[PDB]
Image: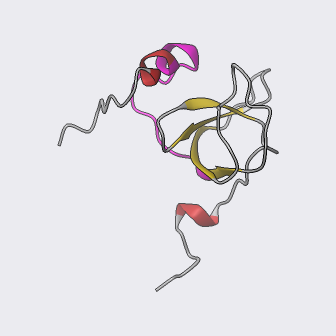
Amino acid sequence: EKKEQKEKEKKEQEIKKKFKLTGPIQVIHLAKACCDVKGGKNELSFKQGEQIEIIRITDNPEGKWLGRTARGSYGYIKTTAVEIDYDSLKLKKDLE
């Protein structure tokens, strides 16, 4: 199907230039932002229990990863602001 552009908000337009995700991006892991976080202008405006996905493991000076909420907001993440799991790539919590 046309799973190329989804266009949810007006946010992904910007993030494609700002964080540079212009094109096809894949998840590296599944994060879940915890707690009350800084979440500034470069960061994702997420929250505690926010189901975000990180698409980019950045080594870039920001010292942040590139994540996105299920709400369609992409942002940098302090690696401490989220719970980064490898489990969530498979989801083996139930495992049935």
In the image, what residue occupies the spot 79% across and 39% down? Answer: 37
Q: Position of residue 18 (x, y in %)?
A: 56, 14
Residue furthest bottom as drawn: 96
Write down the region rendered in magenta: 15-30
Q: Position of residue 55 (x, y in %)?
A: 56, 39
Residue 27 part of the magenta-drawn span: yes
Q: Number of marks in the image?
A: 0
Q: Is residue 41 above or below residue 35?
A: above
6 or 39: nearer the viewer: 39
- Asked whether, in this view, residue 52 is left or right of residue 22, the answer is right
The colouring scheme, among rainbow, by chain, secondary structure or one colour, is secondary structure
- Asked whether, in this view, residue 68 is left or right of residue 1, the answer is right
- Asked whether, in this view, residue 80 is left or right of residue 43, the answer is right
Q: Quadrant of the N terminus?
A: top left
What predominant SS class does the magenta segment belong to?
loop
92 or 39: nearer the viewer: 39
In the image, what residue occupies the spot 69% across and 31% down? Answer: 58
In the image, what residue occupies the spot 58% across and 20% down? Answer: 19
- Asked whether, in this view, residue 37 is left or right of residue 33, the answer is right
Q: Position of residue 2 (x, y in %)?
A: 20, 37
- The part of the image, by quadrant, that contains residue 77 is top right
Residue 47 part of the magenta-drawn span: no
Residue furthest left as drawn: 1
